[PDB]
Amino acid sequence: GVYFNIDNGFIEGVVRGYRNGLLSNNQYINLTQCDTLEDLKLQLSSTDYGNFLSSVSSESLTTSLIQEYASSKLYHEFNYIRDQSSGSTRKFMDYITYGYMIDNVALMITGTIHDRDKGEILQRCHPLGWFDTLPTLSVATDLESLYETVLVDTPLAPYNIEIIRNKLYKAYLEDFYNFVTEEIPEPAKECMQTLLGFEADRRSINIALNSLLKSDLLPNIGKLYPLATFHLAQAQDFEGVRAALANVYEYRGFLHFYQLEMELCRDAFTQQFAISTVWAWMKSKEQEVRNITWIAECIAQNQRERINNYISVY
Amino acid sequence: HFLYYLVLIVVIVYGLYKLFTGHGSDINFGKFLLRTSPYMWANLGIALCVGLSVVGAAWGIFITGSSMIGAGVRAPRITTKNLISIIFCEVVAIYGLIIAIVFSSKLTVATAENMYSKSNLYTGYSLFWAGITVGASNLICGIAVGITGATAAISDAADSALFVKILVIEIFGSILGLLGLIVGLLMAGKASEFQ
Amino acid sequence: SNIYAPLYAPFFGFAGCAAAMVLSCLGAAIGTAKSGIGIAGIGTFKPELIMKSLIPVVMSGILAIYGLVVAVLIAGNLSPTEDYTLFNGFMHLSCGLCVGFACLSSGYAIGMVGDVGVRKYMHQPRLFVGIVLILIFSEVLGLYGMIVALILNTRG
Amino acid sequence: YVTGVIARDKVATLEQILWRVLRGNLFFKTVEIEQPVYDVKTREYKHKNAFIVFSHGDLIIK
Amino acid sequence: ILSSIWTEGLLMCLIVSALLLFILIVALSWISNLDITY
Amino acid sequence: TELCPVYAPFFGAIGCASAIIFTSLGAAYGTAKSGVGICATCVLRPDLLFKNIVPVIMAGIIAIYGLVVSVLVCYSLGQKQALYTGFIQLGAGLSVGLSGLAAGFAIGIVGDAGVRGSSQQPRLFVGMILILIFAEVLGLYGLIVALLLNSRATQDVV
Amino acid sequence: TELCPVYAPFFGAIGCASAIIFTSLGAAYGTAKSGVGICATCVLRPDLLFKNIVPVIMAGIIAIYGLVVSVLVCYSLGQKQALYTGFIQLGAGLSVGLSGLAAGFAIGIVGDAGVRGSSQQPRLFVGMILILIFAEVLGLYGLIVALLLNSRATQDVV
Amino acid sequence: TELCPVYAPFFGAIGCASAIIFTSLGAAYGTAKSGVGICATCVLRPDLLFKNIVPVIMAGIIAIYGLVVSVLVCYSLGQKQALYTGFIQLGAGLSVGLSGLAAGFAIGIVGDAGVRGSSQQPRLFVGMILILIFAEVLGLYGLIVALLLNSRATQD
Amino acid sequence: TELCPVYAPFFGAIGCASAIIFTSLGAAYGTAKSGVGICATCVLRPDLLFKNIVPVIMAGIIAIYGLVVSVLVCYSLGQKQALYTGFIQLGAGLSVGLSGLAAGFAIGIVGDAGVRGSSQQPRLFVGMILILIFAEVLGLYGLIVALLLNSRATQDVV
Amino acid sequence: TELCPVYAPFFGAIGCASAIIFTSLGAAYGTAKSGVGICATCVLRPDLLFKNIVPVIMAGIIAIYGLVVSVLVCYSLGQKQALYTGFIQLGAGLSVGLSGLAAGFAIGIVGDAGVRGSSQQPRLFVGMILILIFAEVLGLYGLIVALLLNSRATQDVV
Amino acid sequence: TELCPVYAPFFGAIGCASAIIFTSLGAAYGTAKSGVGICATCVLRPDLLFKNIVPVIMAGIIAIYGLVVSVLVCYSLGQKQALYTGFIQLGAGLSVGLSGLAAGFAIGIVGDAGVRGSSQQPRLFVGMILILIFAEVLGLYGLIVALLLNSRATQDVV
Amino acid sequence: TELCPVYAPFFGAIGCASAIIFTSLGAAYGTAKSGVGICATCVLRPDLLFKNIVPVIMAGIIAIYGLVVSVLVCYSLGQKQALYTGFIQLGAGLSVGLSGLAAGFAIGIVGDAGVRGSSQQPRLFVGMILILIFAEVLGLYGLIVALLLNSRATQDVVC
Amino acid sequence: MTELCPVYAPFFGAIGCASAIIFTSLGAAYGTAKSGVGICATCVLRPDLLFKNIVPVIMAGIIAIYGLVVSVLVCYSLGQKQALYTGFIQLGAGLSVGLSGLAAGFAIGIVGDAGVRGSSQQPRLFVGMILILIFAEVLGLYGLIVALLLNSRAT
């Protein structure tokens, strides 16, 4: 790891400085005792968020507003790191956003197939995956038409609505699996094969869990590709997938997906000359912008029973 | 990459060409080391002493400097508290500088006769390999102190839990550089000037 | 004078204490730096375990002292004013290759053990005697190269 | 025929999407706008370009 | 005499011009990295 | 002379050095891969003090195959020796080092990938060490040749 | 002399060493490659042991193919041997070496794949061993030409 | 002498060894890439295993293409052979080896596709087998210029 | 003499060997690449089984382009060759080989794409082989200069 | 003879071979990437094969250029030719060889670009030929100096 | 004669070869790289065809700088020419060659740069062509030094 | 003779060759890289075109440095020249060329970035030109080396 | 000529003069190119720091000045009939400011690119930037000191 700090030294030093802004398990105990959104704003400014709500009023402080200012503060940091990267890392951070724009073309089709507005639907769309053709999504509702018309110029071009979603997403995750084993060096090889495999795991389990052929729409890059793909392909009931998921020692008893993700993410920061840190920060800060939102929904309406479901390993 | 396996075929063919035709004693590295000027070896050991020392010193500096500038975007006090990690990367270049000053004093003009004698070839080989010893040991200690002082920068983001242990292995890389210094001062310890 | 002691013979003696020092401190650096990567991902904040988590770096500094003793012991046989044969120039070159690549092997092996192993005998203090016994076999590759060096020093 | 103005950085992608969606054989005309104006969403003076397309089909026009 | 074509002066001029070509080609590789990755 | 030149101990020194460099590159490859593999998923059930050290101590048996031949060719070295002595102890250094390089190459790959599956069932210990001594006899085959070449570096050498 | 020069045992020593070195590197790629596959299987391995060790025991035979020729070349290795002898016993060691290396490349990549289907279907063993015999007679074709080069290495030498 | 030097059996020795080694490097890659596709497909059709050794058999017969010339160049090596008959003996060995190695690669790459495809149509077996024969007569083209070249060797 | 030395056959032997080796390598790439796409072609339409045989046999004439040259170079080899007929012997066949290597690269890379889309159009019986007849005469251009060199090889040597 | 040596027709024969090999490596790369862009686009146009063989046909012409210079370098060889004749022949063969290789790289790169667009619009390949003609002309600058070199070789070489 | 040796026309023969090899290889990277960019954008606008083939013309002006050198250096090659006038011939060939290679590397990249963005803005054409003049002149700088070196082949070559 | 061998104009012929090869390779990298950063931009603001041609005219100037030395290290060539002069002509052409190339890389990489970042702010040009000046001086350092080095050629030379 | 002063002896000197300026100018180029791409990405939105953030390319240019001084100093000691003693001290001064000024110019490039992207998100890093930057600069000055010291022993 003597060549990493050439192009990725300032990059990793600032990403490792962003994971100290991940507010810890003591930083939620004092943050779950507010009962008003103003008070939460008052003591969220002491963190490394650092008074990001200094421009909004206090009378009109919506629950969503905190969800989108904290995510805008996430996403400006992401494309702050992204436009400072070399050709082995600018691609890797683009391949992070390629799985986001699949969830954006999956939502633009299922929003434009029904009677809905472009502007209102566009607001919900995730802004890291955003190509210039994505605001259209209205030339045709046919799946075949979209590829030639609108997806031909995208970087989704080498890759019914959920059927073409998993058809894009499996070929994406296969192409993202054999990229991180080709051009990314040794301390992030074992990371971007295991962490990525986990993402293939909890998507392939959600295939059979949402289906209750299926062998072509399931990604095969993880630990369930050789053995559990055939057992999970012919599972028609919940007990068939419950018996098929017992073969893996790391997934037995789970059928708890994000808790296993965050525990697999806290070991990703244990390496310190790897580029798996920026994925661990992205999924950790995207975790703690839905932890803050889960707390602020229990504060906006008084739901004091189910607050302690936030999950922080860092 | 193909040119490595093309200049290896030439060395095999030219070796077996000299060997099979009875003239394999023409490829003699001894007469090469004995007709070659000692000022070549002595000053390609001085200039590659301070050369590879600076190359490792700078290799350490942009590893831990570009780490603690990135780590200093949120915690700016690290760059004036973890500047001890860029001291020992740069004392590597000091150790290649001291060797250069000491070595230079053994670098005098020799006469026409007494030029390819025993002591002149000795001090040519001695300043050559000692300048490589302290130049490449300081290249490795500069890289080592850089990659372990860069883990001192992203661990001084955490307050005080690890820096007292990290420093111990920071100065363990300095000791290796010093031990490399006192080997090149004993390799050329008995080497005389050019007489 | 001697056919057996040509004037280029200290080239292979200084190439020996060069290869005995640069390679040994290369392996020492790999072991210390690579296990210090594994130390930098831990939190103890307690006494008597700081001095326990520093085993791979005080075991890697012995590899540089293994190279130190050999390089200071075959540069004490080198002097411009006495008989120095080609034979012990070849033996000192082989001493430098033996210690240099054995301490390079020990440093690579204790760096690849000590980067994950320090994270195993910390916050799980029940397999400490297995990880250290791995590091003893992982260190003594260089002590093997030092023993065959010290035979070759007193043999030539 | 339909015509209007866009934000002058979408000409490369409005030509790109209109080239692929009717036939690959359609008419097009582009013209620039001098002294660009500001807006409300961008809050900055952005350039504009006038575009003209042409088609004979009824469902294509929609 | 070392040899008549590969004399020791041609060799010492060709080693200090192969070492300077080695530290030229690696430095051009480092500069080339910027072009390849930016 | 012609049979015993001055550069004749070059091949002997190279052979002696060669056994340690190659043998210890392979013993470090065996130790480095086995240790990481043994401790990747076995953080649970803390009753595994002496669970899998048998690839590590057997790459140390590899490295003492290099040390035995290295001391024994160091006894045969001498200022006035033949090219034949230097040649066949270069071959007796190359065979041990290269063969035990391959032996520790085999030990490393087997150990690194075969210790992960053990964590679920401790019945792998019967069949692991059976296929893990076939890799070690590759080094003992290297030492047999070296120790039998070394038995001819003095028989009628002039 | 001129038929039996002083560098004549260099080819023989490299040749004798090469058989052990090259054959072991094949037997180590056969052992390590096949070994990971056997270790990975655990639910049927203790039920169906002594039928997944046939790649690593066939690969091991290649090593003793290089041992039985490297001992056989080391008997004819001498100080004043002819250069023809050193030439065709470097040719013996290179033939058995790089063909045992080819036969270890075959068994290593053939054998690991076979275990994978052996865990899914127990009627793959007869289709695996038949391929893994053609991958091992390939090493024996190098042996029955190395021992035939060695049968005339001291026939009518001068 | 001049026409028959002492270093002439190096060429013949290289040729005898290269022919066996190069050809069985190609027969290794032929049984490698085919057999890795054979045992991965017989879990669905265990009755059609005996019609999937035909990529392996062809590779095994180019390995005896390499042996039947390497046993026949060994028959006329000699202490004192001419330099012509050392030159063509590597000529013959190289011709059967590097051509045979290519033949092996062709069988292996073509064979792997055929065995995997064979699970869908039993009529594909006659088409795939025919292409393979063409890619194995390349090995016999190397054997014709191995045997014919070898035959002249000892005319002068 | 100096015009007809003792090392003259080696160039000629390389020429004879090169024609067989380089052309076969080109042909093997022209056969393996062209028929690697059979599975896709026959899993949908098995009627196009008799179209993949054309780029295979067009490389088969590429292989006997080098087999004719190498058996005509072999008839002009001799112990007491001139040095001049060694260089033409090397040139004849160096060219047929490396140009049949380019013609087998071209045939095996356009017969892949010509059969990867042939299932969607039955009217490509001429347009594929019209590209093949230009890519296959690239080796015939090598042959008709390997036979003009071989006509000049022993014409006026002395 | 010191002015016309014995090794003089080496690079006259290598100079003859080089033109064919380099020229056909470019006439292969020119028909390779141009031929894979036609048959991958004729699945939607049955008349796609017509008029898309201009890139392949022009690439073929470059091979003719290397043949017309290889049959003129071949008819100027001889056992006693000048060393200046050999150098000129090497220069001429490399002149049309490494420039027809560049004129085949240029056609192979403009030969797949104009195959994905000509199917979308047929009224565009009147400029495609013009851009491509320059590449063909570029090859013609290889023989228009090679031809001069061949004529020069014949005259007053003593 | 040591001023005019026999190996002296070697440097002139590869001075006239390499004056078009690197020139038409830079003009091939000039025409292929610019060509892919122009062809891709020509399907969107058919009428802007003759206005966009100026990087292909300015690639051919490089390729005729290489020929106007390669003819002028061809007119001073002789069997009894001086070593100095093979050296400045070599110098001239590499000067027009590797600078026309840089000047074709420049207008290939700015060729498909300027020809792709002209379809969205028809005003970026006077700025394109001044960059192409700037890039083209470098080749002519190499043609100036290649014409001043070739003037010096006559001045007292002895 | 001894000081003036026949192989001595080899190092001057590749000194005047490499003096314009490695400067045209750096001037080509400074022209092409800047040019592709020209045409990558100036599709939304095409009226700003004669104030980002500074890296392209700057890169061309580097080529001139090579042409000045290679027309001036060519007027000292000769059949019978001393080997010292050929070593100077080699050292001059390598010092202007390999530093010209460095200058070209410097204003190649710096140039595209300035031109593309000037679309979002027109006041970047004030320090952009200064950065290009500093990058340009390296080429002139290689020229002012190879002119002092070329002045030593045929100055108290003996053949 | 004689045994002390052969004809290939000013090759080392000429190569050294060339090496001193080509290797420092390659390192100063890499320093300028990475700092200039850090500046021309930094001051797109923060244009008032345009004179503080330019000190990496000034400081990388000082490496070029150091290289220039060595080339001029040893070209003053060149000559046709020079000893081979002074040939290798001009080559030692050449590649001792050479391969040290390229590594020092590289480290100014990486530290200066990290600094000018870091001293704009937080301006308190500007004092920490240059003190690291000076260290990566005087490694080229340490190369220069050896060259001056080693050129002081010519004749």
Image (spheres, coloured by chain):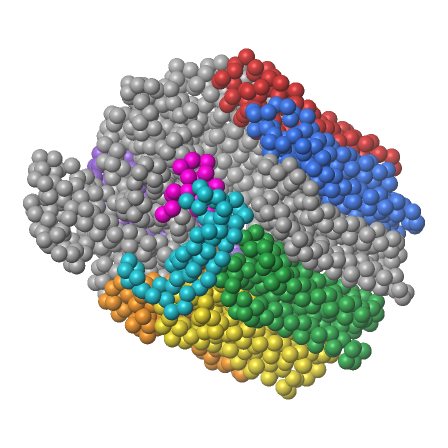
Chain colours: C purple, D cyan, E brown, H red, I blue, K green, L yellow, M orange
Stretch of the chain drawn in magenta: A135-154
The residue lying at 59 percent from left, 25 percent from top is I45
Quadrant assignment, res L85? bottom right
Q: Is residue L55 above or below residue A266?
A: below
Viewed as shown, does residue K148 lie left or right of A64? right
Residue I38 image position (x, y, % from top left): 60, 28
The residue lying at 30 percent from left, 47 percent from top is A119
Residue K145 image position (x, y, % from top left): 67, 74
The residue lying at 31 percent from left, 27 percent from top is A210
Quadrant assignment, res K82? bottom right
User: In the image shown, does M2 or A194 lie closer to the viewer?
Assistant: A194
Q: Is residue L132 visible?
A: yes
User: In the image shown, does H116 or A277 lie closer to the viewer?
Assistant: H116
H75 is within the stretch colored magenta: no
Residue B127 image position (x, y, % from top left): 48, 66
Q: Is residue H77 above or below residue C13?
A: above
The residue lying at 70 percent from left, 32 percent from top is I125
User: In the image shown, does A182 or A201 lie closer to the viewer?
Assistant: A201
